[PDB]
Image 1 (cartoon, helix red, strand yellow):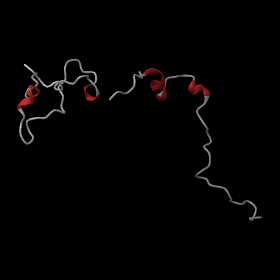
Image 2 (spheres, rainbow over the protein chains, first blue to last red):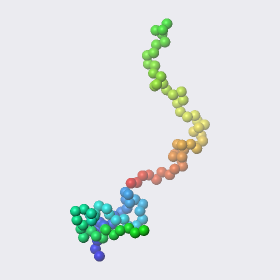
Image 3 (tube, rainbow over the protein chains, first blue to last red):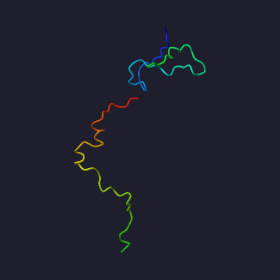
Image 4 (cartoon, helix red, strand yellow):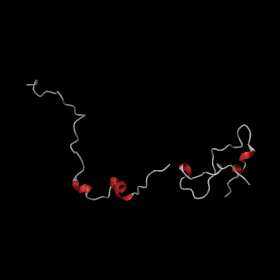
Length: 49
Length: 48
């Protein structure tokens, strides 16, 4: 019930320009490096069509 | 007589074109290539 304040892009710009809803931030650590960090698991939720 | 008819300064590759620009009647139509860009297509600017 508490995510990193930087999980969601604060504003839609650059390649997110013109998007409508909330767009997740890519510059936060992912799970496929040295090890995954449990503090950034809210950002692993996946897209479904 | 052949000393006359000199060649100094002559370069046929750098000669100016015998037409300097399009005539006025062509510019009075506004239905060509430049015309779609200048008059038709929108110009909102590039943001990226």
